[PDB]
Image (cartoon, rainbow, N blue to C red; front, side, top):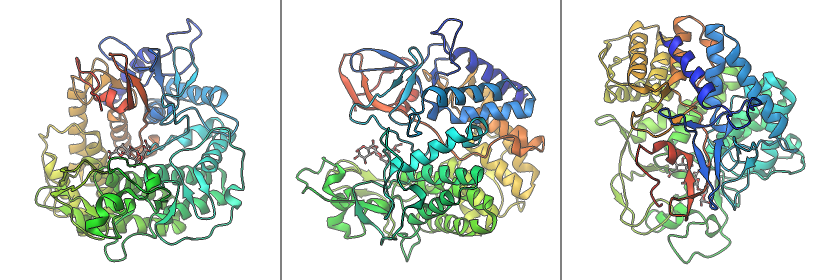
Length: 543
Ligand SMILES: O=C(O)[C@H]1O[C@@H](O[C@@H]2[C@H](O)[C@@H](O)[C@@H](O[C@@H]3[C@H](O)[C@@H](O)[C@@H](O)O[C@@H]3C(=O)O)O[C@@H]2C(=O)O)[C@H](O)[C@@H](O)[C@H]1O
């Protein structure tokens, strides 16, 4: 029984990931990682040898959705109540006067001391990148505190409201400026600014402002959310429709002297490394490379499709922008023959098997940019895009991904010539999610029966020592694992209650800083992502 499995999983989390450092007066906070064998909680090791237990609430927002979903479907209110208690404790103790929380890329809470920590010395700042926190829950706990966060988020990350210069970093303790009442002057594509308008951060701004509109009817918030979304659409290639990862370029204020020094103050990093051979269109925003294309055609897509639907008539532009970009990506970059995307520049330039001729931001000289497999996260965005626009081009990509992933043939069109593989070994939560989307739009039973198979596979192979892990050899389980989320989405569909589980937008959290190695030296730019990829007996590799 899949609901029984998720219930026991969340019970394990609330046992093994809980505050064990304050006696019989624990906080409601949770450790991000637990070794499921021993119950050892994942720790950050600071330069001077001090150990903190990593509690980063930005990295627990899938769990929060899982806890809410489990309460809804099972009728047991303890998981909802605990998630509310965690939210409340963060507004109570870990929200600064500006509204910002001690979470995100560079701040977390030590579960042992309950103090906010900052692992990155130079960057004691607020940062969210494809995080998509569960704002619906936060609003239900404390709407004023949530609203204060979202406004303080925009206040810190918009450097210049006139031109919408944005940054992935935001300073704590800033006073409130003109915010939504700021005057706007639309600038031409790729104007030069200090702030780097990466779409991973841009995603979080758009999403948060839209949720402030959703809950408080804040028209200022919706105006700016849509305006920011449009910033990423206006510089799209007029011929290809591809792009963009950012809508500004780094302002050059020093002349570069070394290729491997890729600080943004030397100017656009793609123009440095690609400009001599490719010309003016080699710009960061135009580099349709692996990772960037997930942020653009997965994370951004999932959020904007759901937002576009929510807004009814005024969401029609959003839906169009979103589906058009997915079409362009499928048209130019997708290789039907082997289920790959081509590394590309947004001008339509194919970069497949290109050898980098000098060092730079995108790799060392001699690095070869290769086609990369279209992952199951893309199956979701193409399945969802097709649901609103039944284009065979969108169906082609979904069909190609599924086939490559051991799922069989989903058909020539939904319900036509379907030969899915009911004996699949696929245990990918992303694939489960996308099959549930395919099922919802078409009501073709085979898609949901395939989703049931993936769920059983998840339970059989990824449910280990009461946790969910992508491999049986992994040292630590992540309490934010999406395996239980996909299992609950399936339960909700079968029970005819899809609204019992929050819509899945493929958000996730991360922590980054200096991490003290076992030889006493500092490993700069260490991510908790790297810690969750370690197997038993493996140590972090010098970077
Ligand atoms: O594809 C990858 O390798 C990753 O993209 C990640 O973000 C990139 C970059 O790799 C990070 O180092 C980070 O870079 C910024 C600045 O560009 C850099 O000069 C320096 O100042 O560090 C910065 C930082 O924020 O740490 O961010 C960019 C980005 O596009 O966000 C991405 O976060 C990661 O998950 C990989 O997919």
